[PDB]
Image (tube, rainbow, N blue to C red; front, side, top):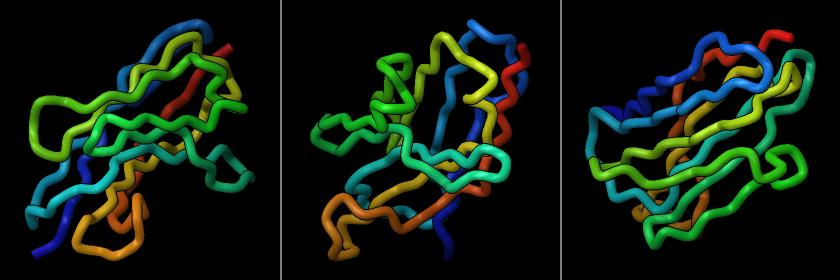
Length: 123
């Protein structure tokens, strides 16, 4: 059928607080190349956040992450966590999980997307 990227761990938190985003793939099974997170603040462009490859290679939008966030592969099939610390009101955005398929030619490219989950960081 279809690939579904189920996102959780979001919600409301106070500035300086933490969140642990989780993305678990369901539906049609696929061999993942890379899984990561994107986000879109109100009235702004959707931007990259973090990603981990199936080899364990990690990359970050360091200019916005600033070493605060840590992505990692979970034990389960196509499951990824994003540990977000020291959150600020500018981190308030809709966060999208994205997954890359090995069966799709582009290397470390993203093919499947989650519906998005809300993250709101109060002052």
